[PDB]
Amino acid sequence: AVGACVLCNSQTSLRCGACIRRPFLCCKCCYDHVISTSHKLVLSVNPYVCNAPGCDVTDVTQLYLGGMSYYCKSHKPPISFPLCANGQVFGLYKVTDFNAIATCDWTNAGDYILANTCTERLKLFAAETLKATEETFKLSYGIATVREVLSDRELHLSWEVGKPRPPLNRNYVFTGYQIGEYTFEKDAVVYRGTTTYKLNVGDYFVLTSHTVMPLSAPTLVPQEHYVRITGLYPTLNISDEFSSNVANYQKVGMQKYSTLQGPPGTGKSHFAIGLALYYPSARIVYTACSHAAVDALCEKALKYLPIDKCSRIIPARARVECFDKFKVNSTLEQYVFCTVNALPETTADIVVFDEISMATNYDLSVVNARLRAKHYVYIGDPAQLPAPRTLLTKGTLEPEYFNSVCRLMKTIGPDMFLGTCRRCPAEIVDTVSALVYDNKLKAHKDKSAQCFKMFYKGVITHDVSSAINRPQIGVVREFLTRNPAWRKAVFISPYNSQNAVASKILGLPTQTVDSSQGSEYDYVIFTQTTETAHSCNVNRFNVAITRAKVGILCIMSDRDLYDKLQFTSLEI
Ligand SMILES: [Zn+2]
Ligand SMILES: [Zn+2]
Ligand SMILES: [Zn+2]
Image (cartoon, rainbow, N blue to C red; front, side):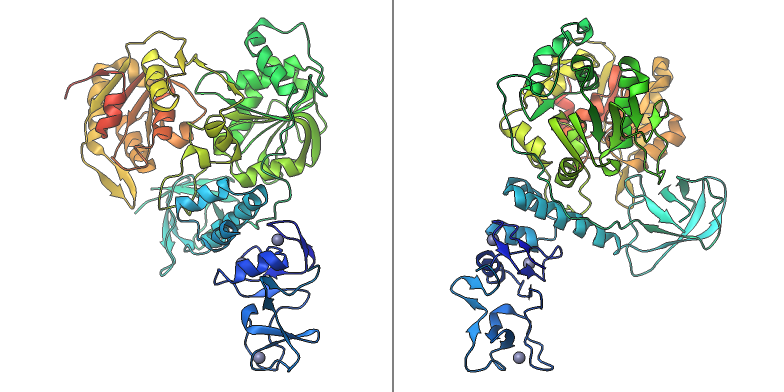
């Protein structure tokens, strides 16, 4: 009932009753809120409402204090002070940007821009408000009731009329009735049940609207520089493998937090797990937003770190299969590998946060509020894909606005930059180096002479809003008959529905760009599918073509990105 003002920390009894989060506002800051917004309900121990029976005046600007009681202009006694006077709202202990965060619906890019250019307290208010807004939107979607069960991987769905039907991909996980979480792909629909329950007729599926806890810890703790390595103990016997990262590993020990920008295949995994071998006594908690990123870090630890001193932290709600080779849920092991949402409350010599472009400011705050650590290391790449913003429909979110780390990396530069790509044929390294890395990314590999492009707009059909280009898949089919080395290729495209079609016609394994991130395949076939903003996004384009170790075929729709591709062009 009494806390600190989210804009200046000044003590107060005043909360805004109109803000979805109900932030504490001091008398000065609460005034400049209610005088500039549709927000006029103020809360104290008792709410600021006229006390006259049956009176419905709740607007703080139309109210007064009558002794220790509140009344409107129509009910106030002769001796009454206005609640809104000389730049203040009356409360105990007696912002433009706060107003925009408080009142925005989060459908505009400028909203996320402001959520990342504002003060640090207003970054937490923004992340709360947004995450709340994201959840109360999941209510807006219709329920899906099973009409009939066909097979162990297909059924027919009946959708609640009046309420819209959510996009039917992987980024939308339903809660089934709790028969465990479930996902669907396209009148027969393919069902993927986290728990193998023999789907019954009438059983209904609904989207998981989780309760948005409030944020306490900053996105980033304040930066500390040291004179010498602090609370860590280096080796002077350090494997030649990791000799390239010794100067970076010493920067990590001589700062509170550090930023590593690592373009595809520049040895992020290698750097993170090498940090443990360089400070071999140090307790490290390895965290990322996804189970895939954390399981990636587990595979690298398995190779180089002692398996006994490693534990994979899995929450009791088993959502996806993940890493098996460690001891599970031993929080006290020197090496702990855990998704941000499952982190325990503990401390660490070093916390390593990986896949930092996929992290929200909400994730940056949670991490700092569960883990107290001597050193924090932020590993990722602002030139890769951000967390999907399900509410954002107007404007494109630039990398400098993904989170506070990406903002740092794009403005003051990262602390450390892995600058040599060991994965990709030079054709791919040269293209993305120019596209997103201002020509600072170097090829270790030679040109493969197995990187082809083809400009072929084909024909764009849609399943709802997800795009399909059958002619582009026809061009791929033709290529495969003449290029049998590509039989093993991973088919990639920016659209599930295109991948679904390509799966049936080609029989190739299938990946969206967004699900391909952090993976690598010998051969990649990418069809752009459309000329949309989604399919032309340079971060997405970067990830798509940097999945390939040996070869890539890009069938393109965008003249620009086709011409940028430093690949051999094909005819037809
Ligand atoms: Zn408000
Ligand atoms: Zn204040
Ligand atoms: Zn009244």
